[PDB]
Length: 205
Length: 205
Ligand SMILES: [Zn+2]
Image (tube, chains in turn blue, green):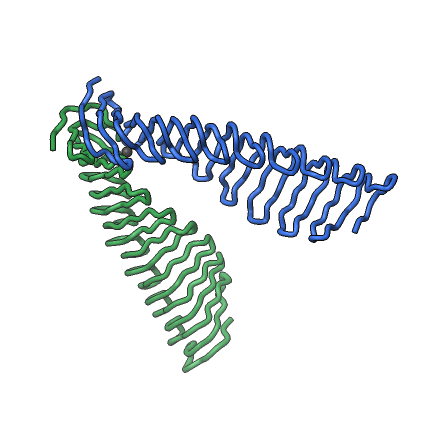
């Protein structure tokens, strides 16, 4: 069903269209394709209000999911792409680069609880250098692989004023590391499974 | 206004009463006083459903506040008193002893975020020995004054597997303390404002 403007033999102008699956589009048409600005209500409850080109979401658009989520940002050919903000169901926001619907490039994750992250992303996960700052003041800085602390990094416990500098495997302190205390002293040791299992030396300030 | 049972010259039996301030009571009456079981709707929106003696809340009763809170437990002469559970607006529960509407005696505070406390209370605040366990695994054990860590105590950081044993002032590590690490080594030092400001010695396992 179509209720709107016709030009030549195509839908062209403004009009509402009801799709075979039950979706509904109201907005701009050009040569029989969704093109310009219009809103689209999906059978699953998702709603898109934004810009279309050649029957696809393209340009700036807002997708209010029914599962509570909400994306505001840029699209190319029906996939989020470029700069955009995802507000998760429970308040957390991602703000940064997207590629083919995946977080890829540079981005922030601002959590509701006060925590905050900024770093490199790839394949929808933290991959590369990034800083995680907790609300209490704890902070990680270093390499990430697959959303986990992984590689060379520094973790600072704001409670004790101390900092670990060493390797991380799968989000856990692993191997030979340095433990710097607030007073400047260091402890060289070996970590396994994120736990200090052997102290080898005590270095002075 | 009263709508209910009369015996002799007093309200006696079951009946509804509307008070000059707008409160409403439906329930049991004995010799013209609220006595037995009945619910009372307050002008401010608070509702009490429970037990009364001699015109006062006395026995077991539930007070659903309008500000979201909710007390389930025991009353004596219109004040919470004895064992009772307070569910705070945002999920936190106190479960333990009350005296004259104040937390006093032994009690738990089960927080929504996973944290948990149990210890001695006085004048509505933690006073005496008590253990605080955080969701991550951090743990305090020792003395409390006025809802704050205060006196001799032990604080364990589950991240670093380390533990501070020393004095606390106003919830902050203060003075000469011992810093025990997971491997058994200790660091004797001085803390000021919760921060390690001088390391005096390094003790072996
Ligand atoms: Zn720590």
